[PDB]
Image (cartoon, rainbow, N blue to C red; front, side):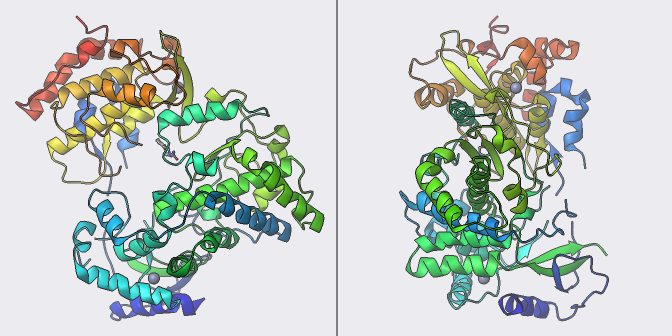
Length: 581
Ligand SMILES: NC(=O)N1CCN(c2ccc(F)cc2)CC1
Ligand SMILES: [Zn+2]
Ligand SMILES: [Zn+2]
């Protein structure tokens, strides 16, 4: 308790000695409260004018226009202690899973040098503004690293002074850059060295773009078994137990020397004990603490979510196969059955899954899995939008399984080769491309962000008639040589290479499911969904608004060219049959 967080709490108290007040009207039941102090501040979504001007028909579609307008009752909840049989299943599974993941990988420290190179090309390493402006400045100043050194030796002593979270179905906890470095130092290897790659973890999909995920689901479908299950968890990060955090910390068992002690400190001092500052309007800062739930950086969060999801889904598979009879208690013979199951079929059962953080698809041995719910509920991983003891509804067709906010279509090229393509309701895609985050965007920066969306559409969503047309229009309206941008970043569309050359590299040359490597010579060789399937997934094809937009598209392109001004532009519209004269 307060010995681990006291020092952190004692330090904040004294930067605000002209404020500290133990509020009696504090709203916390599950978060431990420590005090308050004086503050006052708040980033709302802005519209991308280049994308909106080139998507006029969607100006009257509420599902698009409402996306640009405008659960903290879930963070203040309390997951119960699992039973002893559940705790034993999780510890045995976690111990086996870290060994499998570590067979072909070496844990290692990430460096000041790697951290610097990343901050100098923008990943979302959630830091704060304030002694230096950006992270980009702090990383050059020896002051910062001296501060990092102080905290580091403190962590080696089993103590913490400055690793404090900041709060803001989405709750995002920023720390100062120093604490983010120490996390990266100790645990960055999980992401940097691809521990959750499909090759290394069998269930995972780390480094897999949307052009891979559909092929992976189709390979899972080829397994003998029952339906494909894709149950979402209700608020996964809020259901991570202290038991889960202790099983995750067992990765330290594979480490050595300094690295081991540094990683143990991150787990002990910042994950299994947390200190958070929160803005309450009644505007005072609430310094609160808890032991459980997920509060790491987003990249470490992704890897530990993947690990604990893989563990939970193997245990649900064990329950469906009758490996254990009750979660109340494991017999000695049932522990040896679990261990022997993992050794005998563990890797085969991982290969039955596709797991991206809290997202999963499982193709179990048979449909007993659907009603195998005691371990899943007792681990606290309660299914979203279904009654707690109602059996899961599975999918009979891999093309209708939801995963990573998509479904996947099988599309046959005029030459017989098979594309497995990502898809989602088209209003969602248009709605997202019409939004920018943050302020002070120039017209050139706004245009380069529109071009990033247009190029993503050409590569991933070429099979949607409206998106291939709108992508060609945006790429015609934005100067040919301007570089696509994004203030939050496999993204093969982030390039000034010709999009047909990138299409060939991604879908043909580098595609391990495609045996015939014959390059495609024009966009007209690249197929669409059936016209009715395109409408089912939200196409406006057949509407009067869409026909007028398509026919008059050069007028829209010329409106945006006139706003940007006298620049070099390329006409991409004749890459499509209907404009090719
Ligand atoms: N291999 C992976 O684990 N990622 C996960 C995130 N993912 C994604 C999710 C939603 C979305 F709208 C677009 C892309 C890409 C694949
Ligand atoms: Zn610390
Ligand atoms: Zn679709």
